Image (cartoon, rainbow over all chains, first blue to last red; front, side, top):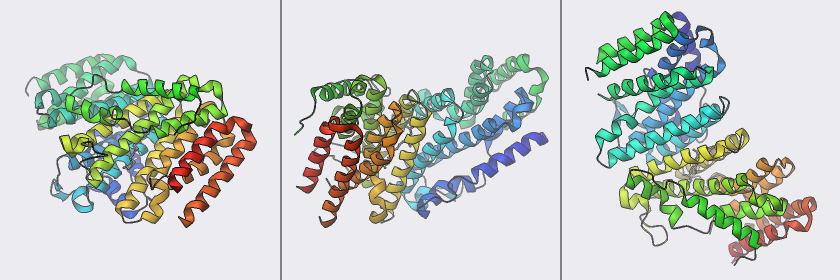
Length: 234
Length: 243
Ligand SMILES: C/C=C(\C)CC/C=C(\C)CC/C=C(\C)CCC=C(C)C
């Protein structure tokens, strides 16, 4: 990716590394930080920073944009911790989970602590951002309930897609480019459904990328590559 | 029982009505049932009662303010979130002769329901301003730390973080909303002690009731006899704790 995005991503990583740094008791801090400290892909923050750079290169190092990327990664951590408890997971890709190592109680309380932290950070981004994240959370909750209730098809859109779309929507709300929201939402949702795993899914994504390109033009390159590259995997 | 103003009881009915709207048409059904369980089998509505009674004593006209009614409902929702999660952590299959949501649907739904409620409360708090939102998130983190200390076998340090933070928010929210910051410090002390005392439902217990009396006295010096219904309520809660 572009050097500027990589640099942004480093600030985000440094910001995430401070979360819970002095949290007490220690059992809570470890449960909170496990998924911050274990090596991850940082898909969501990356999608957000690259989408920003593509739409407004100037705003890449904007403090609100960096904080938003951190927020979306913290909400992803909350989802991991909760899924571990829902599904009683002992491992997540070869690595023992917080619930396995520290109990379900600590895992739950750490997700609560992180939701509050996410909210504290979101407040600075304004009321529209806070309300939107809360709507996102209610969609994820509904999806989990739908899955527990035996409706994998109805739960597909609400299962993990909301965070991916939030990665694309937050920068739009923050920067004021509301005209791209409806498409960014649509794309994020398709990207999300694809992620859980099918030919025309990477086709629509192609179209929505098209519409977006008709708005920002070629400045969309970096983001198109990432999507396309992410597209190739599937 | 309750010797409180009919205006406070009336406000409480409107809070009950607002709470009855929460998650009304929510799907799926198991989510709706888990979410509304502790709202339909209602408790003593102590947290909303404290907020409303305190508001009435500081500013009587504000008991009809939509923001105050919303704040009362939010404090009850967070209490409901705490019940749902506590059911799961302590494995309660019944909570006062009634099957708990975790027992009926499994731990997953209780947790998810709590998640939906946290989100719903944030949505409601946004309408009350950034300070309310920030404050509630700080309350949430304290509750978290409190519960962690518990699980950690640290009842000592857990005393003030486990439930007190919500009792405190019942008194501090209305002050923030009405911009009466001068009383916040005392409201926090008072609320924290009331919460510590109310945790159980002896030597120290009276030392605590004495401290509360002094915080009440400080509020009285500030608002005069208008504080009387709140004072009766605190003395009543103190009473049962000492019974
Ligand atoms: C027994 C008590 C426990 C387990 C703590 C429950 C945690 C609660 C009730 C707080 C949930 C609220 C948040 C995580 C964020 C709330 C912030 C706003 C509504 C602005």
